[PDB]
Image (cartoon, coloured by chain):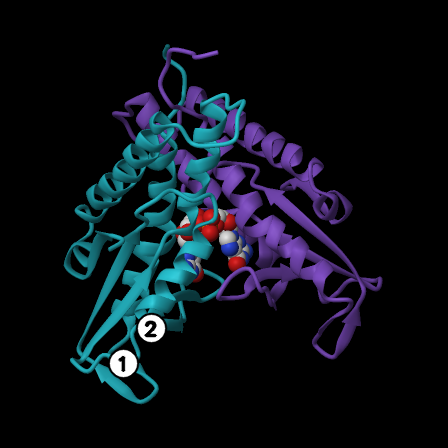
Chain colours: A purple, B cyan
Amino acid sequence: GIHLGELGLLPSTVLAIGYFENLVNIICESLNMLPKLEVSGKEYKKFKFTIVIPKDLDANIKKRAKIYFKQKSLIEIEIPTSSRNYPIHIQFDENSTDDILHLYDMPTTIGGIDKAIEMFMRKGHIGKTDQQKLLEERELRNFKTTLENLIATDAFAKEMVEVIIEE
Amino acid sequence: LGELGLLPSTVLAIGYFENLVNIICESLNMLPKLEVSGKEYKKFKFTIVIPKDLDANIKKRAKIYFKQKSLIEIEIPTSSRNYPIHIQFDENSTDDILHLYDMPTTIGGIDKAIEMFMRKGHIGKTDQQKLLEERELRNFKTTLENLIATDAFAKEMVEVIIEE
Ligand SMILES: Nc1nc2c(ncn2[C@@H]2O[C@@H]3COP(=O)(O)O[C@H]4[C@@H](O)[C@H](n5cnc6c(=O)[nH]c(N)nc65)O[C@@H]4COP(=O)(O)O[C@H]3[C@H]2O)c(=O)[nH]1
């Protein structure tokens, strides 16, 4: 029945819902809509999408993702989609050893969580306390859990998507 | 009572400002001059259009709105991200201002949050759900405007309006 209470969620839950709906699902639908995908003069019929959750929660995950992609020598790839007026931009491994197109992303939306955490702590000093680190790790775990639960509900995503932790 | 938990509109507005608004402003101010298809612009204005109604899929609503406004896609390169920015602009303007537009797709997430919050057992939106949706759209707009006030570029060149 009716519950007294205010609208309120973990930031990781809302950000993971958005990430699944507006990137994961459209990637899977694009790759399953085309009977075959071709990139850089090579054809791919099988795909894997790996979502890399950052090991530490930095406010700027765009920088962290750039560093991670550079370290792994992954390069940009553009995948067309009919669900959006601009294509999907992700990373892939041109050094793969199979006929599977291995795609990767580190969700930049995660960065926002850090801001939320700071407001929760009413931070008055420079530096991350072990309490802030604990809250960050808890949020990273919840983001991963929510994403995996959403992936389990979709046949496309369950077939081709995995979620791992950085390093 | 003292647990981490926020309005979805707050979280989504923070993400939208950091990972789109600010990077648009920074990319466009890096350029020594603004040019598209050989035309020169002396200013740019970025207009963020908040939806009138809260649909789960804001891309569809944005497509309808942009089609009504005869706005077309534009790709803006950026060094703040490993892929360029994609928004809409007015190719039929004649006044030397680069008119850029976006309807925040991230807003769609609010709908899901509200639906789970309502413990819905029937098809249809009660007036309480609609009131909550409108309140969340207002809070998204307010949070975005407060974030824009903290940046000289965004304060100067970004505006936030409601659809229609
Ligand atoms: N590697 C990669 N990741 C993607 C892509 N599309 C979405 N994502 C990821 O999914 C998250 C949610 O995207 P959104 O719901 O559309 O919510 C987006 C979206 O509403 C907007 N936004 C960001 N970039 C753009 C853009 O280039 N064009 C437009 N029209 N909106 C953008 O800002 C919001 C927040 O974006 P993020 O915090 O960065 O968070 C994004 C990002 O982590 C993609 O093409 N490539």
Which image quadrant for residue A33? bottom right
Residue A86 visible in the snapshot = yes
Task: Describe the element under mark 2 as helix, strand or loop.
Answer: loop
Is residue B129 placed above or below B144 in the rendered structure?
A: above
**Quadrant placement of the C terminus of chain B:** bottom left
Q: In this view, does A74 lie to the left or right of B59?
A: right
- How many residues crowd mark 1 within 10 Å: few (<14), some (14–19), many (20+)? few
Q: Residue at x 25, y 60 (%)?
A: B47
Callout 1: chain: B
Q: Position of residue B111 (x, y in %)?
A: 44, 37
Q: Nearer the viewer, residue A48 or B79?
A: A48
| Residue B92 numbered mark, or none | 1
Q: Do the numbered discs 1 and 2 sit on residues whose CB atoms are within 8 Å? A: yes
Q: Which amino acid does label 1 sit on?
A: Asn
Residue A62 visible in the snapshot = no
Mark 2 sits on what residue? B70
Q: Position of residue B11 (x, y in %)?
A: 37, 36
Q: Position of residue A61 (x, y in %)?
A: 47, 47
Q: Which residue is drawn at 52% across and 36% down?
A: A56
Marks 1/2 same chain: yes
Which image quadrant for residue B108? top left
**Quadrant placement of the N terminus of chain B:** top left
Q: What residue type is labelled 2?
A: Ser
Q: Where is residue A17 in the image (x, y as percent from the top left)?
A: 53, 38
Callout 2: chain: B
Task: Describe the element under mark 1 as helix, strand or loop.
Answer: loop
Q: Which of B34 and B135 is in front in this view?
A: B135
Residue most extreme to the bottom: B38
Q: Nearer the viewer, residue B112 or B143?
A: B112
Q: Which of marks 1 and 2 is nearer the N terminus?
A: 2
Q: How far apart are marks 1 and 2 (CA)?
A: 8 Å
